């Protein structure tokens, strides 16, 4: 069980490789692209939007990711150009 701290942060993008924060991720709005923002060392960004539209996030290296606008949203970056299946099942021998 990992104890998570509750702070005043808006959105959070992390990679699905090791579990680290995304630094330098291009995140913009569906209609408000001009007001696009990037992620910090912590893996979060700050953006103010009037309408409750969706937010498009992209980071050079891993697959793209999109999430709706909310007080706290977690995103996971999937490996790009890499096919890795994480499935397993046992039974009769």
Image (cartoon, rainbow, N blue to C red):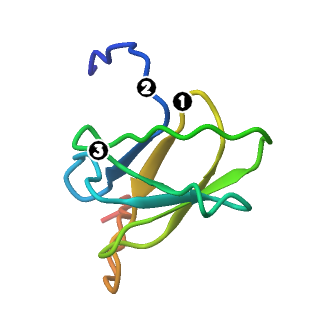
As measured in the structure, the alpha-carbon distance from the residue carrying label 2 to the one carrying label 3 is: 11 Å
Q: Which quadrant is the N terminus positioned in?
A: top left
Quarter location, residue 17:
bottom left
Quarter location, residue 69:
top right
Q: Which residue has dot 3 on it?
A: 40
Q: Which residue has dot 2 on it?
A: 9
Q: Nearer the viewer, residue 40 or 89?
A: 40
- SS for tag 3? loop
Above or below — where is 79 with respect to 19?
A: below
Q: Residue at x 49, y 57 (%)?
A: 27
Label 1, residues with CA under 10 Å away: few <14, some 14-19, many ≥20: few
Above or below — where is 60 with respect to 12?
A: below
Q: Position of residue 3 (x, y in %)?
A: 28, 15
- SS for tag 1? loop
* Callout count: 3
Q: Is residue 79 left or right of residue 29?
A: left
Disc 1 or disc 3, which is closer to the eye?
Answer: 3
């Amino acid at each position: 069980m990992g104890h998570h701290h509750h702070h005043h942060t808006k959105g959070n993008v992390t990679s699905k490789t090791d579990g680290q924060p995304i630094i330098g991720a291009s995140v913009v709005e569906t209609t408000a692209t001009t007001n696009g923002t990037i992620t910090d060392f912590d893996g979060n960004f700050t953006l103010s939007v009037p309408v409750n539209s969706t937010l498009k996030i992209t980071y050079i290296g891993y697959k793209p990711v999109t999430v709706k606008a909310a007080a706290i949203v977690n995103v996971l970056l999937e490996e790009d150009t890499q096919m890795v299946d994480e499935v397993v099942v046992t039974g009769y021998t």
